[PDB]
Amino acid sequence: TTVPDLESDSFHVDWYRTYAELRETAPVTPVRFLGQDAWLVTGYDEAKAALSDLRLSSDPKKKYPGVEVEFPAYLGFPEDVRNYFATNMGTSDPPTHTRLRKLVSQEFTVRRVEAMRPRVEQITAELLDEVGDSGVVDIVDRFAHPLPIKVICELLGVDEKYRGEFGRWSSEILVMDPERAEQRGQAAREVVNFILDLVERRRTEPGDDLLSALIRVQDDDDGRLSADELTSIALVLLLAGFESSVSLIGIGTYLLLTHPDQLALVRRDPSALPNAVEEILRYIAPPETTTRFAAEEVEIGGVAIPQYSTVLVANGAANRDPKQFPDPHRFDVTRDTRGHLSFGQGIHFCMGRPLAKLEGEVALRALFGRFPALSLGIDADDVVWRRSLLLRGIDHLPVRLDG
Ligand code: HEM
Ligand SMILES: CC(=O)N1CCN(c2ccc(OC[C@H]3CO[C@](Cn4ccnc4)(c4ccc(Cl)cc4Cl)O3)cc2)CC1
Image (cartoon, rainbow, N blue to C red; front, side):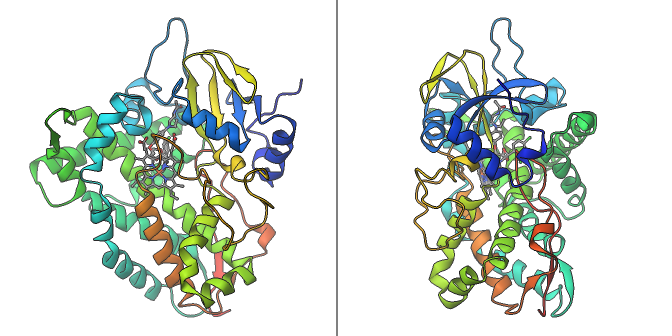
């Protein structure tokens, strides 16, 4: 039987049509990717089931007798840089996952996030002043990208004379191309080196930022974060702040710009914004794929997945499963979006949801509430989508401010 190759253009060009074709045939099928066999889950019920079954591990560090685990997200990473990337909540299983998440949740709170609202609003205003009131600009470079970066750097106590470079490395890591495995491995070593220096500097000069708080957080029973745990968690938070919300804002802008009717609703009624953000996430989920490792043989949707198999849960495909979302390919800011898998599901449910929703709502409201005639600078079909199954997005988006 023909086995799909996630590297082919079928998974990067009008790819939701490809997912729909595989789903109708089999919501759980074997695929090829980066020279390795794996299983792709595209059905909603199957994806939800997979993410809820703890026999499917999230820890790339675990060793199993006679098997060589090589996960996509760590293509080209030397073993030591891999460990620095994989010693945090997202890359661990209970009970380790449990204590790491409890310690971090003590400081990465809704209160702390809400306290940043005025600042996020100020930063948004300043960036929009800087773009002008007429002409064509790349809204990604001048807005969608700088906003989340400034926010996450103030949250983690990262200086300006350190940014710019980091963003160059982040971008390389989002693409998984075997021809550039070496450059990817090099960019990853750069980020590890940067984080190590940042942490050490913070231990020496404490502040009221999140990294400082994480450094002294401790619990009677759970103790405190080890040096390695601290380092990996900081790395992962900065990485998420540098790339996740950029996709949301850029993709969000492109969608509202290509659905005039939908944009009107938002403009007409502001209370319709929070749900618009949820539908945007539902329609084109940035984390198109999340990975799991079958520590035991598991059955998903009637299909038996052999032990030691790599499972790619396609969060994005599941969001377009007609069985859960009627008329899936229809972008509708009013539909009921409950249950989408863009923020995950279960114990690893994304801890940054509050921050992402804040940035998304504030940015889009300000952007469109300030450029009534804002329109796309190019033809809708000419937009270039980033070729990443790790984090989908738009790197360049020209828009005409004055119409
Ligand atoms: C558009 C924005 C975002 C989306 C769509 C998103 C999506 C996701 C998804 C799907 C997962 C679960 C992955 C899995 O099950 O393996 C996840 C986990 C996580 N995300 Fe996000 N995320 C976003 C923003 C953020 C932000 C702003 C931060 C932090 C500054 C962040 C921090 C995390 C962490 C720490 C985890 C691991 C949670 C755990 O394993 O317990 N995310 N995110
Ligand atoms: C077994 C295996 O291969 N692994 C690969 C993916 N895994 C993972 C890793 C980290 C994670 O914290 C979210 C931190 C970690 O994940 C990213 C993706 N992300 C963004 C927001 N929420 C998730 C991320 C991760 C890796 C790479 Cl290379 C790039 C990026 Cl932007 O940011 C949560 C889960 C778990 C499964």
